[PDB]
Image (cartoon, coloured by chain):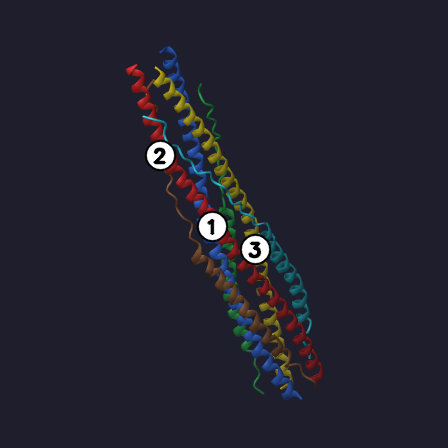
Chain colours: A cyan, B green, C brown, D blue, E red, F yellow
Amino acid sequence: GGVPELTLDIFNATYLNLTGEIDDLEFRSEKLHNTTVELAILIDNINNTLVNL
Amino acid sequence: GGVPELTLDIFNATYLNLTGEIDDLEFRSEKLHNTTVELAILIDNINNTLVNL
Amino acid sequence: GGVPELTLDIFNATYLNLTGEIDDLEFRSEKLHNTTVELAILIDNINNTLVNL
Amino acid sequence: NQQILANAFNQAIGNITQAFGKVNDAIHQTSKGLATVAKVLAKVQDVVNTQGQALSHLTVQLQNNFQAISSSISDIYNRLDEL
Amino acid sequence: NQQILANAFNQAIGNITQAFGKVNDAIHQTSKGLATVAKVLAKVQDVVNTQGQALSHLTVQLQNNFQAISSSISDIYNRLDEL
Amino acid sequence: NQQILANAFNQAIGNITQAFGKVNDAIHQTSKGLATVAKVLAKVQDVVNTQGQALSHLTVQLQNNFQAISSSISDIYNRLDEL
């Protein structure tokens, strides 16, 4: 018996970078929030147009 | 030759627990569904206000 | 001293297949886009009904 | 003038109902989208956690193995030195 | 009265169009959001799967290595006992 | 006729405001949903990256270990052959 073959593949990690996407999501979620505020305004405005004849 | 240094770092796993978020998503998806049902009602109601003069 | 017990559990990978979901998302995102185009049309149509008496 | 206004109103209403219908479709789509995300998460959690667990267990096993190997080598050298 | 109603209608219409515009913006945002999610998934799938594959391959390799080491040690002890 | 139209308008308006309210609720829900996704991503990124890093480091360590073991075995055989 001789020296055994002990091969081992080095794993070279590919890192998951999601910060841009993050982020992009964050931006969408706050844009939707701001839309809710504006829409509340516009809704009360539509309510103000009820006629009293 | 002596005994070789064979160090090996134990990996202590951090478990990903997404059940709250899950869940929160689930809740949003069903709230949006319920909104669709209410909106169908309100749409037919707006349709009922067509005048026939 | 004898031969040491060197057990090693083979890890049998379960592959994450997200292509259907992908995909389903893709489909939703384009349906929402198409909705934006139709809604732009309908909005200009509502704007055309302003009376000039 | 009154008929004109009435006609305008009716036109507006039809268009408004159509617009709301489109928005409803969009809401439906969003609902579906979020549910899909929720499902995907479950899958990822499981695979990821499984992998982490295996990795952890693997290192424990490896530590044991290497410890045993070290002991074995030490004993071998003792025997060799006695020879 | 008729002019009043007409004015009310016009005001309502303007506001209604604005409201629909805002909702359209929101829908656009949602569309973008879902697409981003779709992209993220691709990335995660790939990294996660790659990691799993590597881990699996790693264990196979390790099993082979340890088997060879065990054989080697056995042979060494045979030689030592013959000595 | 004019009162009729006026009544229709008012009814339409009430319903329209209610509809917009519902859509606003939906938009709010969507906002929340996207933020949750954003948070989840952070978590996944971290765990996944940590796992990858550990795996990489683990293989480097293993390579070192096996290299040392190979050297050791070679030396042992040299000693045995000298015996």
Q: Where is residue E11 in the image (x, y as percent from the top left)?
A: 69, 76
Marked residue chain, label 2:
E
N-terminal label among 2 and 1:
1
The circle drawn on residue F34 is: 3
Residue annotated with mark 2? E64
Q: In this view, does B24 lie above or below A43?
A: above
Going by the numbered disc 1, the residue's amino acid type is Asp
Residue annotated with mark 1? E46
Q: A23 left or right of B12?
A: right
> Which one is in front, D81 or D69?
D81
Quadrant, the N terminus of chain C: top left
Q: Is mark 1 on a helix, strand or loop?
A: helix
Q: Nearer the viewer, mark 2 or mark 1?
A: 2
Q: Which of marks 3 and 2 is in front?
A: 2
Q: In 3D space, how far apart are the residues under numbered discs 2 and 1 (Cα atoms)?
A: 27 Å
Does residue B42 appear in the picture of this structure?
Answer: no
**Residue positioned most to the front:** F82
- The residue at 28%/16% (across/down) is E82
